[PDB]
Length: 124
Ligand SMILES: [Mg+2]
Image (cartoon, rainbow, N blue to C red; front, side, top):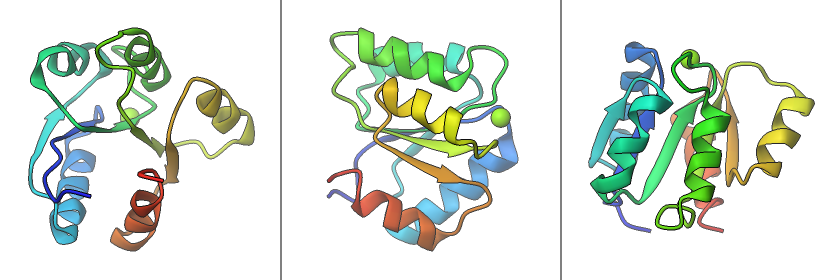
């Protein structure tokens, strides 16, 4: 589990993107880039050669479940594991997201400890 998979962090909230960049940094992961909406993650995704996606749900460009679908449907990208960060903790929301192919889930707030527990287990 490389402290160096290249990770895309998607969220319409810059402070959120950076609270996340640092807990990842605390964890041994530095290689990170950001995107503020799914509409602007995909073309990053499409040729950036990433290894892992962490994305929010609530985004207005392209909501996060939609990005996940475009990923699952792009043949070059559907092998990517996606951790989803959540805003609104509902069992009807999670179901729909597992149904769309998400690898794991996490609920805000979260800590660098709930985070690794979530990591050790996607690559699972
Ligand atoms: Mg959001």
